[PDB]
Amino acid sequence: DIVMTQSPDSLAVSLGERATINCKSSQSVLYSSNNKNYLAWYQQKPGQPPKLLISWASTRESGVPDRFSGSGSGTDFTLTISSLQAEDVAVYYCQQYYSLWTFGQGTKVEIKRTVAAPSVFIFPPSDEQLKSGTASVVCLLNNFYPREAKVQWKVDNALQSGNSQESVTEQDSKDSTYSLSSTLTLSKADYEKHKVYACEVTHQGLSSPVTKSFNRGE
Amino acid sequence: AALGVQSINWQTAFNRQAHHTDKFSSQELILRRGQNFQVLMIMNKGLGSNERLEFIVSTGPYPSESAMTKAVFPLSNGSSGGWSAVLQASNGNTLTISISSPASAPIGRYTMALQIFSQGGISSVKLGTFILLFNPWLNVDSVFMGNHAEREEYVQEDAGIIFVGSTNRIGMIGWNFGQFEEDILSICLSILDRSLNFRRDAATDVASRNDPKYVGRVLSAMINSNDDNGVLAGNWSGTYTGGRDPRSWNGSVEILKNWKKSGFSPVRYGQCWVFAGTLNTALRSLGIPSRVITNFNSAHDTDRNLSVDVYYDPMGNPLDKGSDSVWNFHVWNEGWFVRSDLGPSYGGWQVLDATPQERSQGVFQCGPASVIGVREGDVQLNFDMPFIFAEVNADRITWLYDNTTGKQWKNSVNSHTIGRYISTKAVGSNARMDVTDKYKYPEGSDQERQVFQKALGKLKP
Amino acid sequence: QITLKESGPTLVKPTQTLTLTCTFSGFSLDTSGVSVGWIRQPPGKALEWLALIFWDDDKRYSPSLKSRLTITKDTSKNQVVLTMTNMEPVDTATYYCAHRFVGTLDVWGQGTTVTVSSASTKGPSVFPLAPSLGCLVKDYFPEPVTVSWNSGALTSGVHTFPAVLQSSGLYSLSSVTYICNVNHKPSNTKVDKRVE
Ligand SMILES: [Ca+2]
Ligand SMILES: [Ca+2]
Ligand SMILES: [Ca+2]
């Protein structure tokens, strides 16, 4: 197998600026016979299949904006986005098709943007759910940048651990923000044993931590 | 005195004229096998009834009665076939004697001795040496060619025409075969004595010189320098420093002489018509009727599939892939003989090619290939039939090759472009005779395509 | 007009044989030079080419997985079928089919998710997330689940979070009058839920 190794693994650039991605192959994909490089670039936006940008190292496919351009030969190739646009946020793979098909591991390209503090929201368990015997408390962090954020659950000021799970959105293709969800799961039994449920958030866009809490039974 | 021989008269000019060897510039007795010759042998006295003569003939360095490179035969009153001596007349002490060789005798130089038994004593005395050649005049010889006018062209003619140029525009050059010039027959016999076969096992090589198939194949090797320091070194480079430009030769005679006089060191340089010219001289000298063939758009098939392969990628780009090629023209030879190895239907013209193209059994040599066999696409028969069939009748196939999957598939076929205007000089003129129809059925017939499939079938036994 | 569409079981129990179909239009797999291929993508990982079939029934396979793989075509039904034996949890991935001609794999299908597990299908519970808004889609097996709001009328500002696999071996996710439309095709459980 020819081995495709991309670099970097992640890239954050400001709008309008140049983003470059290297790809390297374990062997040469220059076929001398026709003097063509058997090397493609793809773009995969989250939740879709991949989309071919460039074949033969440098030929753009139909409809691909000219801000995308491929260069390189042999074992060293480069995809260069000339003016990064909000919607260019995606994972880019290189692929050789000289000897069957192998892909690179992917490179995430994200928009660098000014810091944005999250909107925090907390949600008590549903009465429907309490019947089924479980209590899920939810915390929402809305429309922040950068991605790095810290969520801590406290129940009557006891710091929780073991019982919570988090989930983040992909960078918005419009405003280049993220959002985050944290889910604290207790048994109904445990839920009733305590009063104050708190969700403490540290984010760079907050000058100091913001805590949203609720009292059981409103 | 005991019976002894005083002198022998070989009647050289008489016998050479009868044996159609009188044209050679040479002092020697040159004979053809299977045909009697007459000598006068002057003894010291008349023969007694106690007295016996035995002739002994031998050829080559390890003569053997079993290998038929030695023969011992009494003077008798009756012909035996085989080697024989018949007393035709006594006149004083002179014996008139008719000596006969078999049609199956190995060709080459022979020694003759006489052994006399007289008064309870034995004497042996070397009588002389002669050259024995193939006999195209003799009905029972494998090289027999019954037509008078054709024999004159294919054996006795020492000037030739070789067709050259391209399939758009055929030219000609003259070639002086010169088989009758001084020393040339001698040099051509030399070639047989310097072959790899001879060096490995001279006793068996010499025994095999009764077979034109054998001699022909050997010559196809030995005319090229490759493997064996044969006669001609090939060079298609355009740079001929340290030798002659292949185009400056106009005959075989300088080449063969220069080979001998350099101590049998390859003559520099030849291309395909020079090999063929020189091979033709050798064949005619030894008495294998032969001629020179030119094939236009001649295929070099390097992978035994009867097609010249050309490659494109699926986007239509030409690929540097494959080693098959097509020559403007290529020149080779035909020799005339039966093929006892193949059967009655495969006699006649046999392809021999001295130009070093492909190794055959490890050696640059080629043929004999039955021209009849080639036309009928019996390419399983000896020798080199696949290669020769491709030369005249390869399809030209364009392939698509997808380098990613390693898959090739066939795009198009041109089944008529290879093998055009196959040409030999006409009997008794400088006309171009076309012999394309001898090598293949007609381009675009059903037969032509049937044979092509059949042939292809036999590559894959 | 070149479109490809994948289909088959979204759950396979270990040791059994996954069978995937690719139904295509806009081009013929009787055309010379044309090939359709299969690719898979394990969650949050790199793409992996599996197999390829040509118009003339020539096949190619990933060298490592060849012994397990079988690709076949039916030009009459505009279909390519992939068969993978001895399925194992690692083989959990999105599977794609794609068109090939003269360059590489150039037009792809939507993808179909395939989970390998001896666990059974379970449909989701859907609970409302009190506005004072969203809905919680809890304990569904296997992936995937599609969410919309007001039958697709409401799209702007909607965040549907990726699922999280819980300790229990079941998945869970949240989405942000308002009705959330949750479809879970593996259990045929399409549920529409009101929020307050
Ligand atoms: Ca040689
Ligand atoms: Ca070939
Ligand atoms: Ca033909």
Image: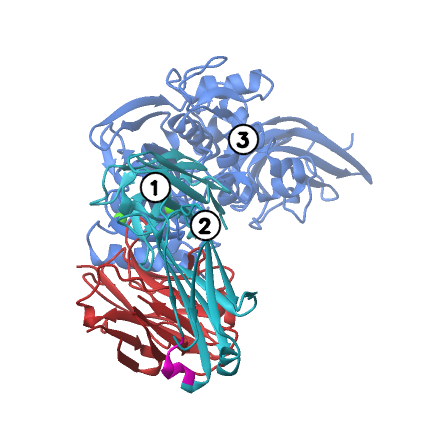
Chain colours: A cyan, B blue, C red
Disc 3 to disc 1, how far (Cα)?
A: 77 Å
Give the SS element for disc 3. Answer: loop
Q: Residue furthest bottom?
A: A131
- For the residue pair B300 and B352, the one nearer the viewer reads as B300
> Considering the image in quadrants, where does the N terminus of chain B appear?
top right
Q: Quadrant of residue A180?
A: bottom left
Where in the figure is residue C25, as x and y percent of width and height?
A: 20, 65
User: From the viewer's perspective, is residue B267 above or below residue B102?
Assistant: above
Give the SS element for disc 1. Answer: loop
In this picture, which residue range is highlighted in magenta? A125-130
According to the picture, the residue beneath numbered tag 2 turns out to be A148
According to the picture, the residue beneath numbered tag 1 turns out to be A113
- The three-letter amino acid code for the residue at tag 3 is Asn
> Considering the image in quadrants, where does the C terminus of chain B appear?
bottom left
Q: Earlier in the sequence, mark 1 or mark 2?
A: 1
The residue under the point 28% across, 80% down is C190
Disc 3 to disc 2, how far (Cα)?
A: 78 Å
User: From the viewer's perspective, is residue C195 above or below residue A167?
Assistant: below
Bin the neighbour count of mark 1 within 10 Å (Cα to Cα): few under 14, some 14-19, many 20 and up.
Answer: some
Q: Is residue A28 left or right of residue A68?
A: right
Q: Which mark's residue is nearer the viewer, 3 or 2?
A: 2
Bin the neighbour count of mark 2 within 10 Å (Cα to Cα): few under 14, some 14-19, many 20 and up.
Answer: few
Where in the figure is residue A197, as x and y percent of width and height?
A: 47, 69
Q: Chain of mark 2?
A: A
Residue C49 part of the magenta-drawn span: no
Disc 1 to disc 2, how far (Cα)?
A: 14 Å
Q: Do marks 1 and 2 share a subunit?
A: yes
Q: For disc 3, does the CB lie below 8 Å from ligand 1?
A: yes
